[PDB]
Picture (cartoon, rainbow, N blue to C red):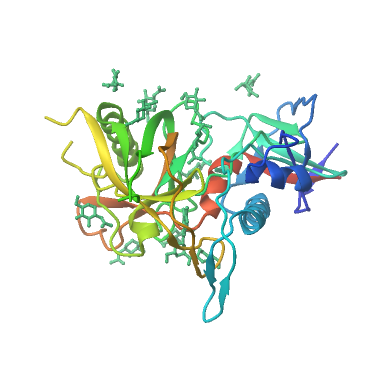
Length: 343
Ligand SMILES: NCC(=O)N1CCN(C(=O)N2C[C@H](CO)C[C@H](C(=O)Nc3ccc(Cl)c(F)c3)C2)CC1
Ligand SMILES: *[C@@H]1O[C@H](CO)[C@@H](O)[C@H](O)[C@H]1NC(C)=O
Ligand SMILES: *[C@@H]1O[C@H](CO)[C@@H](O)[C@H](O)[C@H]1NC(C)=O
Ligand SMILES: *[C@@H]1O[C@H](CO)[C@@H](O)[C@H](O)[C@H]1NC(C)=O
Ligand SMILES: *[C@@H]1O[C@H](CO)[C@@H](O)[C@H](O)[C@H]1NC(C)=O
Ligand SMILES: *[C@@H]1O[C@H](CO)[C@@H](O)[C@H](O)[C@H]1NC(C)=O
Ligand SMILES: *[C@@H]1O[C@H](CO)[C@@H](O)[C@H](O)[C@H]1NC(C)=O
Ligand SMILES: *[C@@H]1O[C@H](CO)[C@@H](O)[C@H](O)[C@H]1NC(C)=O
Ligand SMILES: *[C@@H]1O[C@H](CO)[C@@H](O)[C@H](O)[C@H]1NC(C)=O
Ligand SMILES: *[C@@H]1O[C@H](CO)[C@@H](O)[C@H](O)[C@H]1NC(C)=O
Ligand SMILES: *[C@@H]1O[C@H](CO)[C@@H](O)[C@H](O)[C@H]1NC(C)=O
Protein backbone atom coordinates (compact mmCIF):
# COMPACT_ATOMS: atom_id res chain seq x y z
CA UNK A 1 0.00 0.00 0.00
CA UNK A 2 1.56 3.30 -1.13
CA UNK A 3 0.33 6.85 -0.67
CA UNK A 4 0.89 10.43 -1.74
CA UNK A 5 0.41 13.81 -0.10
CA UNK A 6 -3.11 15.13 -0.54
CA UNK A 7 -5.83 17.28 1.02
CA UNK A 8 -9.36 16.01 1.59
CA UNK A 9 -12.43 16.89 3.64
CA UNK A 10 -12.13 15.41 7.13
CA UNK A 11 -14.91 14.63 9.59
CA UNK A 12 -14.84 14.88 13.39
CA UNK A 13 -15.57 12.56 16.31
CA UNK A 14 -16.18 13.30 19.99
CA UNK A 15 -17.67 12.03 23.26
CA UNK A 16 -20.37 14.67 23.59
CA UNK A 17 -23.09 13.94 26.16
CA UNK A 18 -26.68 13.65 25.03
CA UNK A 19 -28.41 16.34 27.12
CA UNK A 20 -25.46 18.52 28.13
CA UNK A 21 -26.19 22.16 27.36
CA UNK A 22 -22.46 23.07 27.25
CA UNK A 23 -21.88 24.66 23.87
CA UNK A 24 -19.00 22.41 22.82
CA UNK A 25 -21.08 19.32 23.59
CA UNK A 26 -24.11 20.61 21.63
CA UNK A 27 -22.00 21.48 18.59
CA UNK A 28 -20.31 18.07 18.63
CA UNK A 29 -23.68 16.33 19.03
CA UNK A 30 -24.86 17.54 15.62
CA UNK A 31 -21.57 18.12 13.78
CA UNK A 32 -19.45 15.12 14.85
CA UNK A 33 -19.87 11.37 15.16
CA UNK A 34 -19.07 9.26 18.25
CA UNK A 35 -15.38 8.46 18.73
CA UNK A 36 -13.89 5.26 17.37
CA UNK A 37 -14.49 2.54 20.00
CA UNK A 38 -11.54 0.38 18.84
CA UNK A 39 -8.69 2.51 17.47
CA UNK A 40 -5.44 0.80 16.48
CA UNK A 41 -2.50 2.46 14.75
CA UNK A 42 -0.48 0.56 12.16
CA UNK A 43 3.28 0.92 12.46
CA UNK A 44 4.98 1.41 9.09
CA UNK A 45 8.23 -0.57 9.19
CA UNK A 46 11.43 1.25 8.15
CA UNK A 47 9.40 4.18 6.77
CA UNK A 48 10.72 7.74 6.86
CA UNK A 49 8.28 10.51 5.96
CA UNK A 50 8.48 14.30 5.70
CA UNK A 51 6.04 16.50 7.63
CA UNK A 52 5.37 20.26 7.64
CA UNK A 53 3.27 21.52 10.55
CA UNK A 54 3.28 25.05 9.01
CA UNK A 55 1.73 23.85 5.70
CA UNK A 56 -0.98 21.46 6.86
CA UNK A 57 -4.54 21.70 5.64
CA UNK A 58 -5.80 19.94 8.78
CA UNK A 59 -5.09 23.20 10.60
CA UNK A 60 -7.31 25.22 8.23
CA UNK A 61 -10.07 22.62 8.54
CA UNK A 62 -9.95 22.77 12.33
CA UNK A 63 -9.90 26.57 12.16
CA UNK A 64 -13.12 26.51 10.12
CA UNK A 65 -14.71 24.15 12.65
CA UNK A 66 -13.87 26.30 15.67
CA UNK A 67 -15.07 29.44 13.86
CA UNK A 68 -18.34 27.62 13.13
CA UNK A 69 -18.60 26.45 16.75
CA UNK A 70 -18.06 29.89 18.24
CA UNK A 71 -20.40 31.46 15.67
CA UNK A 72 -23.28 29.17 16.71
CA UNK A 73 -22.49 29.12 20.46
CA UNK A 74 -21.42 32.52 21.75
CA UNK A 75 -24.14 35.16 21.40
CA UNK A 76 -22.98 38.74 21.93
CA UNK A 77 -25.55 41.39 22.81
CA UNK A 78 -24.03 43.57 20.09
CA UNK A 79 -21.97 42.56 17.04
CA UNK A 80 -20.12 45.28 15.10
CA UNK A 81 -18.51 44.00 11.88
CA UNK A 82 -17.79 47.45 10.49
CA UNK A 83 -20.64 49.93 10.26
CA UNK A 84 -23.39 47.32 10.64
CA UNK A 85 -24.62 46.91 14.23
CA UNK A 86 -26.53 43.71 15.06
CA UNK A 87 -28.39 43.68 18.38
CA UNK A 88 -29.83 40.51 19.93
CA UNK A 89 -30.34 38.53 23.11
CA UNK A 90 -27.19 37.52 24.98
CA UNK A 91 -27.98 34.77 27.49
CA UNK A 92 -25.11 33.43 29.52
CA UNK A 93 -23.92 30.03 28.30
CA UNK A 94 -22.14 26.99 29.68
CA UNK A 95 -18.69 26.83 28.08
CA UNK A 96 -15.85 24.29 28.51
CA UNK A 97 -13.93 22.79 25.54
CA UNK A 98 -14.05 19.03 24.93
CA UNK A 99 -11.68 16.90 22.83
CA UNK A 100 -12.29 16.70 19.08
CA UNK A 101 -10.87 13.89 16.95
CA UNK A 102 -10.22 14.59 13.27
CA UNK A 103 -10.77 11.58 11.00
CA UNK A 104 -10.16 10.62 7.30
CA UNK A 105 -12.82 9.39 4.86
CA UNK A 106 -12.49 6.25 2.74
CA UNK A 107 -9.37 6.16 0.58
CA UNK A 108 -7.28 8.26 2.97
CA UNK A 109 -5.29 7.87 6.19
CA UNK A 110 -3.49 10.07 8.71
CA UNK A 111 0.24 9.53 9.15
CA UNK A 112 1.48 10.16 12.67
CA UNK A 113 5.02 11.12 13.62
CA UNK A 114 6.11 9.32 16.80
CA UNK A 115 9.61 10.83 17.01
CA UNK A 116 9.93 12.22 20.54
CA UNK A 117 12.23 15.05 19.37
CA UNK A 118 10.22 15.92 16.23
CA UNK A 119 10.17 19.71 15.85
CA UNK A 120 7.24 19.88 13.37
CA UNK A 121 9.15 20.07 10.05
CA UNK A 122 11.37 17.66 8.15
CA UNK A 123 11.79 13.89 8.21
CA UNK A 124 10.40 11.52 10.80
CA UNK A 125 11.69 8.01 11.22
CA UNK A 126 9.04 6.43 13.55
CA UNK A 127 5.81 6.72 11.55
CA UNK A 128 2.44 5.07 12.08
CA UNK A 129 -0.94 5.37 10.39
CA UNK A 130 -4.21 6.15 12.17
CA UNK A 131 -7.82 6.68 11.19
CA UNK A 132 -8.28 9.56 13.66
CA UNK A 133 -6.10 11.97 15.57
CA UNK A 134 -6.27 11.96 19.34
CA UNK A 135 -8.76 14.18 21.13
CA UNK A 136 -7.73 17.81 20.70
CA UNK A 137 -9.26 20.48 22.92
CA UNK A 138 -9.76 23.71 20.91
CA UNK A 139 -8.61 26.29 23.46
CA UNK A 140 -8.73 29.87 22.23
CA UNK A 141 -6.01 32.02 23.81
CA UNK A 142 -3.15 34.44 23.23
CA UNK A 143 0.45 34.39 24.54
CA UNK A 144 0.04 31.11 26.44
CA UNK A 145 -1.12 27.77 25.08
CA UNK A 146 -3.39 26.15 27.65
CA UNK A 147 -4.53 22.63 28.44
CA UNK A 148 -2.57 21.16 25.57
CA UNK A 149 -0.21 18.23 25.38
CA UNK A 150 3.40 18.29 26.48
CA UNK A 151 6.64 17.55 24.70
CA UNK A 152 7.69 14.05 25.71
CA UNK A 153 11.47 14.58 26.00
CA UNK A 154 13.12 18.02 25.85
CA UNK A 155 11.53 21.42 25.42
CA UNK A 156 10.84 21.76 21.68
CA UNK A 157 11.20 24.97 19.64
CA UNK A 158 8.83 25.10 16.65
CA UNK A 159 9.00 27.57 13.76
CA UNK A 160 8.54 27.60 10.00
CA UNK A 161 11.93 29.40 9.75
CA UNK A 162 13.79 30.49 12.89
CA UNK A 163 16.07 32.86 10.95
CA UNK A 164 12.98 34.79 9.77
CA UNK A 165 11.86 36.94 12.70
CA UNK A 166 8.36 37.43 11.24
CA UNK A 167 7.64 33.72 11.80
CA UNK A 168 5.97 32.82 15.08
CA UNK A 169 7.78 30.51 17.50
CA UNK A 170 5.83 27.84 19.36
CA UNK A 171 7.66 26.77 22.53
CA UNK A 172 6.44 23.28 23.52
CA UNK A 173 6.96 22.64 27.22
CA UNK A 174 7.77 19.24 28.69
CA UNK A 175 6.37 20.10 32.15
CA UNK A 176 3.05 21.89 32.51
CA UNK A 177 2.74 24.97 34.72
CA UNK A 178 -0.58 25.59 36.44
CA UNK A 179 -2.34 28.96 36.14
CA UNK A 180 -5.24 29.44 38.56
CA UNK A 181 -7.52 32.37 37.66
CA UNK A 182 -10.32 33.71 39.85
CA UNK A 183 -12.99 36.38 39.70
CA UNK A 184 -14.05 36.26 43.34
CA UNK A 185 -17.38 36.56 45.22
CA UNK A 186 -19.18 39.62 44.16
CA UNK A 187 -20.75 43.04 44.54
CA UNK A 188 -22.13 46.00 42.64
CA UNK A 189 -15.58 45.90 40.71
CA UNK A 190 -17.21 42.80 39.25
CA UNK A 191 -14.64 42.73 36.43
CA UNK A 192 -11.45 42.62 38.55
CA UNK A 193 -9.78 39.20 38.64
CA UNK A 194 -6.39 37.64 39.17
CA UNK A 195 -4.35 34.61 38.14
CA UNK A 196 -1.98 32.81 40.49
CA UNK A 197 1.14 30.94 39.36
CA UNK A 198 3.86 29.17 41.33
CA UNK A 199 6.87 31.43 40.75
CA UNK A 200 9.42 28.70 41.51
CA UNK A 201 7.98 26.46 38.80
CA UNK A 202 7.51 29.26 36.26
CA UNK A 203 10.98 30.75 36.59
CA UNK A 204 12.55 27.30 36.45
CA UNK A 205 10.72 26.53 33.20
CA UNK A 206 11.56 29.97 31.78
CA UNK A 207 15.23 29.36 32.57
CA UNK A 208 15.04 26.08 30.64
CA UNK A 209 13.31 27.86 27.73
CA UNK A 210 16.08 30.47 27.54
CA UNK A 211 18.75 27.76 27.50
CA UNK A 212 16.91 25.97 24.70
CA UNK A 213 16.64 29.21 22.73
CA UNK A 214 20.39 29.75 23.23
CA UNK A 215 20.96 26.44 21.43
CA UNK A 216 19.21 27.85 18.33
CA UNK A 217 20.71 31.36 18.34
CA UNK A 218 24.48 30.87 18.62
CA UNK A 219 24.52 30.92 22.45
CA UNK A 220 23.43 34.61 22.32
CA UNK A 221 21.98 36.47 25.29
CA UNK A 222 18.21 35.74 25.46
CA UNK A 223 15.90 38.51 26.65
CA UNK A 224 12.15 38.40 27.30
CA UNK A 225 10.14 41.60 26.99
CA UNK A 226 6.39 42.27 27.17
CA UNK A 227 4.62 42.90 23.84
CA UNK A 228 5.38 46.24 22.14
CA UNK A 229 2.03 47.65 21.15
CA UNK A 230 -1.20 46.16 19.92
CA UNK A 231 -4.69 45.79 21.20
CA UNK A 232 -5.48 44.26 24.57
CA UNK A 233 -5.83 40.79 23.04
CA UNK A 234 -2.18 40.96 21.96
CA UNK A 235 -0.60 42.77 24.91
CA UNK A 236 -2.48 40.61 27.41
CA UNK A 237 -2.87 36.88 27.89
CA UNK A 238 -6.45 36.47 26.69
CA UNK A 239 -8.62 33.35 27.12
CA UNK A 240 -12.20 32.35 27.89
CA UNK A 241 -13.19 30.94 31.28
CA UNK A 242 -16.79 29.78 31.88
CA UNK A 243 -17.89 31.92 28.93
CA UNK A 244 -16.27 35.07 30.35
CA UNK A 245 -13.34 36.67 28.51
CA UNK A 246 -10.35 37.14 30.80
CA UNK A 247 -7.52 39.54 29.94
CA UNK A 248 -4.43 39.00 32.11
CA UNK A 249 -1.28 41.11 32.44
CA UNK A 250 1.79 38.85 31.93
CA UNK A 251 4.45 41.43 32.72
CA UNK A 252 5.49 39.51 35.85
CA UNK A 253 5.86 36.35 33.75
CA UNK A 254 8.22 37.94 31.23
CA UNK A 255 10.72 39.67 33.56
CA UNK A 256 14.40 38.76 33.05
CA UNK A 257 15.41 39.61 36.65
CA UNK A 258 14.35 36.29 38.16
CA UNK A 259 16.81 36.28 44.51
CA UNK A 260 13.69 37.15 46.50
CA UNK A 261 11.08 35.94 43.96
CA UNK A 262 10.13 32.32 44.69
CA UNK A 263 6.52 32.83 45.81
CA UNK A 264 3.15 32.91 44.13
CA UNK A 265 2.94 35.26 41.13
CA UNK A 266 -0.37 37.14 41.07
CA UNK A 267 -1.31 38.41 37.63
CA UNK A 268 -3.89 41.25 37.61
CA UNK A 269 -6.75 40.50 35.23
CA UNK A 270 -10.05 41.87 34.07
CA UNK A 271 -13.16 40.38 32.48
CA UNK A 272 -13.93 42.28 29.29
CA UNK A 273 -17.34 42.73 27.71
CA UNK A 274 -16.05 44.26 24.45
CA UNK A 275 -13.56 42.14 22.59
CA UNK A 276 -11.88 42.19 19.21
CA UNK A 277 -12.98 38.88 17.72
CA UNK A 278 -10.48 36.32 16.45
CA UNK A 279 -12.83 34.66 13.93
CA UNK A 280 -13.02 37.76 11.77
CA UNK A 281 -12.48 41.48 11.97
CA UNK A 282 -15.00 43.03 14.30
CA UNK A 283 -16.02 43.83 17.84
CA UNK A 284 -18.48 41.90 19.98
CA UNK A 285 -20.15 43.09 23.18
CA UNK A 286 -21.27 40.59 25.80
CA UNK A 287 -23.33 40.97 28.95
CA UNK A 288 -21.66 41.62 32.31
CA UNK A 289 -20.15 38.62 34.04
CA UNK A 290 -22.20 36.06 35.95
CA UNK A 291 -22.33 36.38 39.73
CA UNK A 292 -20.43 34.11 42.10
CA UNK A 293 -16.87 32.85 42.12
CA UNK A 294 -15.55 32.45 38.55
CA UNK A 295 -12.56 30.12 38.59
CA UNK A 296 -10.44 28.27 36.03
CA UNK A 297 -7.37 26.18 36.74
CA UNK A 298 -5.43 25.43 33.56
CA UNK A 299 -2.16 23.89 32.40
CA UNK A 300 0.24 26.18 30.57
CA UNK A 301 1.65 23.75 28.01
CA UNK A 302 3.33 26.09 25.54
CA UNK A 303 4.24 29.69 24.75
CA UNK A 304 3.85 31.77 21.60
CA UNK A 305 6.87 33.97 20.89
CA UNK A 306 7.84 36.61 18.34
CA UNK A 307 11.54 37.44 18.02
CA UNK A 308 12.55 41.09 17.62
CA UNK A 309 14.00 42.10 14.26
CA UNK A 310 17.08 44.19 13.59
CA UNK A 311 19.25 42.52 16.27
CA UNK A 312 21.78 40.74 14.01
CA UNK A 313 24.40 43.37 14.90
CA UNK A 314 23.85 42.98 18.65
CA UNK A 315 24.65 40.14 21.04
CA UNK A 316 21.02 39.76 22.16
CA UNK A 317 17.87 38.10 20.93
CA UNK A 318 14.74 39.54 22.50
CA UNK A 319 11.48 37.60 22.50
CA UNK A 320 7.97 38.77 23.25
CA UNK A 321 4.76 36.80 23.78
CA UNK A 322 2.54 36.97 20.77
CA UNK A 323 -0.83 35.43 20.02
CA UNK A 324 -3.52 36.49 17.59
CA UNK A 325 -3.49 33.91 14.75
CA UNK A 326 -5.53 31.15 16.39
CA UNK A 327 -4.29 28.76 13.68
CA UNK A 328 -1.03 28.43 15.62
CA UNK A 329 -3.01 27.15 18.63
CA UNK A 330 -4.36 24.27 16.52
CA UNK A 331 -0.96 23.76 14.91
CA UNK A 332 0.54 23.16 18.36
CA UNK A 333 -1.52 19.96 18.59
CA UNK A 334 -1.76 18.89 14.94
CA UNK A 335 2.01 19.13 14.32
CA UNK A 336 2.45 15.35 14.40
CA UNK A 337 -0.29 14.60 11.85
CA UNK A 338 -0.54 14.66 8.06
CA UNK A 339 -3.12 13.39 5.61
CA UNK A 340 -2.19 11.12 2.71
CA UNK A 341 -4.19 9.48 -0.08
CA UNK A 342 -3.95 5.69 -0.32
CA UNK A 343 -2.69 4.93 -3.83
N1 LIG B 1 -9.31 37.42 8.65
C1 LIG B 1 -8.47 36.30 9.05
C2 LIG B 1 -7.69 36.46 10.36
O1 LIG B 1 -6.65 35.91 10.46
N2 LIG B 1 -8.16 37.23 11.51
C3 LIG B 1 -9.42 37.96 11.55
C4 LIG B 1 -9.47 39.19 12.46
N3 LIG B 1 -8.62 39.10 13.64
C5 LIG B 1 -8.14 40.27 14.36
O2 LIG B 1 -8.49 41.33 13.96
N4 LIG B 1 -7.24 40.25 15.53
C6 LIG B 1 -6.84 41.52 16.18
C7 LIG B 1 -7.54 41.68 17.53
C8 LIG B 1 -6.89 42.92 18.17
O3 LIG B 1 -6.83 43.89 17.15
C9 LIG B 1 -7.34 40.46 18.37
C10 LIG B 1 -7.63 39.24 17.58
C11 LIG B 1 -7.70 38.12 18.66
O4 LIG B 1 -6.87 37.29 18.85
N5 LIG B 1 -8.90 38.22 19.46
C12 LIG B 1 -9.28 37.37 20.56
C13 LIG B 1 -10.56 37.52 21.08
C14 LIG B 1 -10.97 36.74 22.15
C15 LIG B 1 -10.09 35.81 22.70
CL1 LIG B 1 -10.62 34.79 24.07
C16 LIG B 1 -8.81 35.67 22.19
F1 LIG B 1 -7.95 34.76 22.72
C17 LIG B 1 -8.40 36.46 21.12
C18 LIG B 1 -6.67 39.11 16.34
C19 LIG B 1 -8.30 37.72 13.92
C20 LIG B 1 -7.40 37.33 12.75
C1 LIG C 1 7.79 4.43 18.00
O1 LIG C 1 6.74 5.12 18.66
C2 LIG C 1 6.07 4.31 19.64
C3 LIG C 1 4.82 5.06 20.04
O2 LIG C 1 3.80 4.91 19.06
C4 LIG C 1 7.00 4.05 20.82
O3 LIG C 1 6.87 2.69 21.22
C5 LIG C 1 8.45 4.35 20.45
O4 LIG C 1 8.72 5.74 20.57
C6 LIG C 1 8.78 3.87 19.03
N1 LIG C 1 8.83 2.41 18.99
C7 LIG C 1 9.60 1.73 18.14
C8 LIG C 1 9.53 0.24 18.24
O5 LIG C 1 10.32 2.29 17.32
C1 LIG D 1 13.70 20.96 12.61
O1 LIG D 1 14.48 19.83 12.18
C2 LIG D 1 14.98 19.92 10.83
C3 LIG D 1 15.79 18.67 10.58
O2 LIG D 1 14.93 17.59 10.23
C4 LIG D 1 15.80 21.20 10.64
O3 LIG D 1 16.17 21.29 9.27
C5 LIG D 1 14.99 22.41 11.06
O4 LIG D 1 15.78 23.60 10.94
C6 LIG D 1 14.53 22.23 12.49
N1 LIG D 1 13.80 23.40 12.96
C7 LIG D 1 13.91 23.86 14.21
C8 LIG D 1 13.11 25.07 14.55
O5 LIG D 1 14.64 23.30 15.04
C1 LIG E 1 -2.36 19.09 33.75
O1 LIG E 1 -1.09 18.40 33.71
C2 LIG E 1 -1.07 17.15 34.43
C3 LIG E 1 0.35 16.62 34.35
O2 LIG E 1 1.22 17.54 33.70
C4 LIG E 1 -2.09 16.20 33.83
O3 LIG E 1 -2.05 14.97 34.55
C5 LIG E 1 -3.48 16.84 33.88
O4 LIG E 1 -4.43 15.99 33.25
C6 LIG E 1 -3.46 18.20 33.18
N1 LIG E 1 -4.76 18.85 33.28
C7 LIG E 1 -5.54 19.09 32.22
C8 LIG E 1 -6.84 19.79 32.50
O5 LIG E 1 -5.21 18.76 31.09
C1 LIG F 1 12.63 19.41 29.78
O1 LIG F 1 13.60 19.78 28.78
C2 LIG F 1 14.81 20.37 29.27
C3 LIG F 1 15.65 20.68 28.05
O2 LIG F 1 15.05 21.67 27.22
C4 LIG F 1 15.50 19.41 30.23
O3 LIG F 1 16.66 20.02 30.77
C5 LIG F 1 14.54 19.04 31.36
O4 LIG F 1 15.16 18.11 32.23
C6 LIG F 1 13.27 18.44 30.78
N1 LIG F 1 12.33 18.13 31.85
C7 LIG F 1 11.72 16.94 31.95
C8 LIG F 1 10.78 16.79 33.11
O5 LIG F 1 11.92 16.04 31.15
C1 LIG G 1 14.43 32.14 6.40
O1 LIG G 1 14.37 33.53 6.71
C2 LIG G 1 15.53 34.28 6.35
C3 LIG G 1 15.27 35.71 6.78
O2 LIG G 1 13.98 36.14 6.34
C4 LIG G 1 15.81 34.15 4.85
O3 LIG G 1 17.06 34.78 4.56
C5 LIG G 1 15.85 32.69 4.43
O4 LIG G 1 15.96 32.60 3.01
C6 LIG G 1 14.59 31.98 4.90
N1 LIG G 1 14.60 30.58 4.51
C7 LIG G 1 13.61 30.02 3.81
C8 LIG G 1 13.76 28.56 3.50
O5 LIG G 1 12.63 30.66 3.44
C1 LIG H 1 -7.06 28.46 43.07
O1 LIG H 1 -7.15 29.73 43.75
C2 LIG H 1 -8.27 29.84 44.64
C3 LIG H 1 -8.29 31.26 45.15
O2 LIG H 1 -7.04 31.90 44.99
C4 LIG H 1 -8.13 28.80 45.74
O3 LIG H 1 -9.26 28.89 46.60
C5 LIG H 1 -8.05 27.41 45.13
O4 LIG H 1 -7.83 26.44 46.15
C6 LIG H 1 -6.91 27.34 44.10
N1 LIG H 1 -6.90 26.03 43.46
C7 LIG H 1 -5.78 25.39 43.11
C8 LIG H 1 -5.97 24.05 42.46
O5 LIG H 1 -4.66 25.87 43.32
C1 LIG I 1 5.84 25.50 43.95
O1 LIG I 1 6.81 24.81 43.16
C2 LIG I 1 7.80 24.10 43.91
C3 LIG I 1 8.78 23.52 42.91
O2 LIG I 1 8.12 22.97 41.78
C4 LIG I 1 7.13 23.03 44.78
O3 LIG I 1 8.11 22.35 45.56
C5 LIG I 1 6.09 23.68 45.68
O4 LIG I 1 5.38 22.65 46.36
C6 LIG I 1 5.10 24.50 44.85
N1 LIG I 1 4.11 25.16 45.70
C7 LIG I 1 4.41 26.08 46.61
C8 LIG I 1 3.25 26.65 47.38
O5 LIG I 1 5.57 26.45 46.82
C1 LIG J 1 0.85 45.48 33.03
O1 LIG J 1 1.30 46.01 34.30
C2 LIG J 1 2.37 46.96 34.21
C3 LIG J 1 2.73 47.35 35.62
O2 LIG J 1 2.51 46.28 36.53
C4 LIG J 1 1.93 48.16 33.37
O3 LIG J 1 3.04 49.04 33.23
C5 LIG J 1 1.46 47.70 32.00
O4 LIG J 1 0.94 48.81 31.28
C6 LIG J 1 0.38 46.63 32.13
N1 LIG J 1 0.02 46.12 30.82
C7 LIG J 1 -0.97 46.64 30.08
C8 LIG J 1 -1.20 46.00 28.75
O5 LIG J 1 -1.65 47.58 30.48
C1 LIG K 1 -8.46 23.63 31.23
O1 LIG K 1 -9.00 22.39 31.73
C2 LIG K 1 -9.66 22.48 33.00
C3 LIG K 1 -10.10 21.08 33.35
O2 LIG K 1 -10.77 20.47 32.26
C4 LIG K 1 -10.82 23.46 32.90
O3 LIG K 1 -11.45 23.59 34.17
C5 LIG K 1 -10.30 24.82 32.44
O4 LIG K 1 -11.37 25.75 32.29
C6 LIG K 1 -9.57 24.67 31.10
N1 LIG K 1 -9.04 25.96 30.68
C7 LIG K 1 -9.43 26.59 29.57
C8 LIG K 1 -8.79 27.93 29.32
O5 LIG K 1 -10.24 26.11 28.79
C1 LIG L 1 19.49 40.16 9.49
O1 LIG L 1 19.18 38.76 9.35
C2 LIG L 1 18.75 38.38 8.03
C3 LIG L 1 18.44 36.89 8.07
O2 LIG L 1 19.40 36.14 8.80
C4 LIG L 1 19.78 38.77 6.96
O3 LIG L 1 19.23 38.50 5.68
C5 LIG L 1 20.14 40.25 7.07
O4 LIG L 1 21.21 40.59 6.19
C6 LIG L 1 20.58 40.55 8.49
N1 LIG L 1 21.04 41.93 8.67
C7 LIG L 1 20.58 43.04 8.06
C8 LIG L 1 21.23 44.33 8.47
O5 LIG L 1 19.69 43.01 7.23
